[PDB]
Image (cartoon, coloured by chain):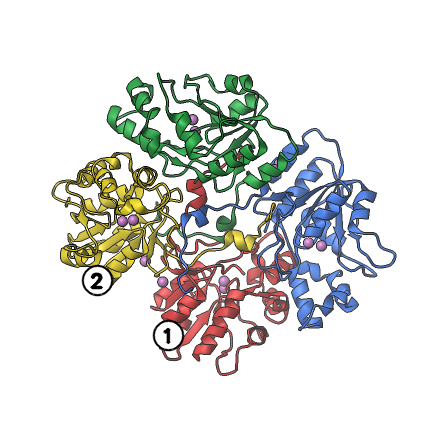
Chain colours: A yellow, B blue, C red, D green
């Protein structure tokens, strides 16, 4: 309607979400020794939509073809991340996990490429000391690869942060703590997921 | 779903409402001389649901019969308002209109009764000086009565505050400024109206 | 404060970190647990009883809170003024759920004891609680700085306690029960509103009505 | 700040007093008005151009804002880096609406002028603006404490100016145009976010994407 109107039941209404803060996560981990933790990349620690938007309009303006196009991946994984914007929620989590002496892992469904400069983009943006840093893991279901879940088990990752359903379920399938970050509403990756759909923790205000 | 989840498009989403504050209304009236203004009663200046809830379960537990039952009205209009809770938004508006030297009118669709102590309940709760106070007007469509709209025109009411659609349209039909107040979500008068449905001003936080 | 404060999208999306839950989530979390005792605070938890408290304030101590230790007030509040008290939908939903479960249902209130009380009847009637689930209201008092609820929750072996005030949640916590918060409506006369979620407790969504 | 801040229903329902509007409301408010000139700011109004600005910061002045008066930066920003700029849906909706109307569409930007610019092409392409509605981007500068937009809006007889920054709204107000606010996304690198609505101006709902 031209003027929908509203009411205070609607204005006050809350979805039943396990919201958490970075400070609550850290509190929850008080006294637990160094452990391995992992992050999804896209919309979790980098707003990488700039590179993906430019891939779609350079390589398949009318489809999602570009995501199976090696010319795109080679560009996305080798410097288009200089236009990716780091998420503040990720700065906060990564600083806290570095303070703990945790090992930091990035596990991505992006297609693998001959070389990648994503690892260095991350370590540089987030100031991750050498001793906490690990090369990006390209996970998936192509011949020769292992799944996200396998890599979590392989690396003994106890906490996995991610914005997509499959990040949470990959963690749950191996008994890790899967924590949800909100995808930004200006991402080009749509529809936005239903954060909290599995009763998982969701980080407040983690869209930026 | 057991865990609906949410996303930040939904968390940030706004209905396109002309929200206003009491301070903005007063600013809008800067330098305008004394004028007559009017208020709906129920859910506008009094949360009167306590009396109406007790009327429904005393007089028609299974219907809305009680609203045509004179035994109810006689009770509702003659002291059940001692359990009605005054709305803070109404305290703020009434104080400001008294400060302006405006005349205060209450125009109600409640059924008329032989006597009424509602006028005194209002003047007492809201501290309305004699010189600003006017006896409650019972408006409607029974033989001998005038409509809300007629009484607005008759009294030269230039601004009419109310929570129901018909308060806004009654004002609009006579060219008055109809300003919406939010019905509380715990009112027994349901469904809640769509505040802002006619592009009218709606007062922020006016549910209490 | 400023005439046109404006706002921004960080503020509009911002969420406090609260363990929000729904009645269905609570019911699921209890699936397969046999009958147990559970407990509810009354005022702003199951009944919007502000009508009677407001009337009492205005009748007996217009300029203060003395009415709340005035016996003549309590006698009115506990023997008919809850006829103006509006049942909360969250309470109807939770009480139906616990009856489904076969749980014993207690009401534990800091209202002062009176010679008679028709509050037990009002609650049983309003919420259609069967006799086997219903228990007489327990009137525990205030008494600063004691929580007069805790000992009742221990005595009745209450495993879940719903309430809108901080002391409802801490009473539960004192006894190892699961304290679950209901939001106090903004038009309550009991002010200021508590910070639901301030102990990391579950808070029921939309529970202000 | 506290580990479990909690919250309450006054806070959860609370609204700032903003003149929110929708594109449909704006279109209705213009029904029967003949073609006119209208204008848009670019950055965070029609394009999320933070990718290029972020890259520019990091390339040319990592520890400061000096890149924004560095010509080598502007030359990159205006000649290809908007290939990474993400069009805003609010902008697509508004620009389609103004084209429907037959309005002339201007882009007025405080980005610094460069020798060449492919920003006009990017916008025309991205938003499918026909040649008759499209106008070359107007690169006005910053220059504190001057608003370098106002004179352009007067020169082009722009009657509506959309923008996310306070100076977009005041430029409009300076010329008697109708200034309409778009929300800046919270993941913009241009911080802090402005207080949309702080001049009593219309603010477009959901306009952060
Ligand atoms: Co992702
Ligand atoms: Co009303
Ligand atoms: Co209570
Ligand atoms: Co801008
Ligand atoms: Os938790
Ligand atoms: Os990913
Ligand atoms: Os206005
Ligand atoms: Os009425
Ligand atoms: Os839970
Ligand atoms: Os109590
Ligand atoms: Os408007
Ligand atoms: Os600009």
The residue labelled by disc 1 is C31
Quadrant location of ligand 7?
Answer: top right
Say which quarter of the image contains residue C82.
bottom right
Q: Position of residue A175 (x, y in %)?
A: 22, 63
Could you classify mark 2 by the number of other residues whose Cα lies within 10 Å: few (under 14), some (14-19), or many (20 or more)?
Answer: some
How many marks the image carries: the answer is: 2
| The furthest residue to the left | A131
Q: Nearer the viewer, mark 1 or mark 2?
A: 2
Q: Is residue B31 left or right of residue C201?
A: right
Q: Is residue A150 left or right of residue C140?
A: left
* Mark 1, secondary structure of its residue: loop
Say which quarter of the image contains residue B20.
top right
Q: Position of residue A41 (x, y in %)?
A: 25, 46
Q: Position of residue D95 (x, y in %)?
A: 50, 34
C199 to A208, vertically: above or below: below
Q: Is residue B40 visible?
A: no
The residue located at (45%, 22%) in the rendering is D136
Q: Quadrant of the N terminus of chain B?
A: bottom left
Most foreground residue, B155 or D200: D200
The residue labelled by disc 2 is A174
């Amino acid at each position: 309607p031209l003027n929908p109107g509203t009411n205070v039941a609607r204005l006050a209404e809350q979805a039943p979400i396990h919201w958490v803060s970075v400070a609550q996560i850290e509190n929850s981990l008080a006294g637990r020794p160094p452990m391995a933790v992992g992050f999804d990349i896209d919309d979790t620690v980098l707003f990488s939509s700039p590179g993906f938007w430019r891939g779609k309009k350079t390589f398949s303006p009318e489809s999602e073809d570009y995501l199976k196009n090696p010319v795109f991946w080679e560009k996305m994984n080798n410097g288009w991340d200089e236009f990716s914007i780091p998420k503040e929620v990720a700065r906060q989590l990564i600083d806290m996990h570095v303070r703990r002496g945790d090992a930091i892992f990035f596990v991505t469904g992006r297609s693998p490429t001959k070389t990648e400069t994503v690892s260095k983009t991350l370590a540089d943006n987030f100031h991750i000391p050498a001793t906490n840093m690990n090369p990006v893991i390209f996970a998936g279901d192509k011949p020769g690869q292992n799944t996200k879940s396998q890599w979590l088990q392989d690396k003994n990752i106890r906490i996995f942060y991610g914005d997509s359903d499959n990040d949470i379920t990959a963690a749950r399938d191996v008994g890790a703590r899967g924590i949800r970050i909100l995808r930004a509403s200006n991402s080009t990756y749509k529809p936005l997921p239903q954060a909290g759909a599995f009763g998982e923790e969701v980080i407040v205000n983690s869209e930026y």
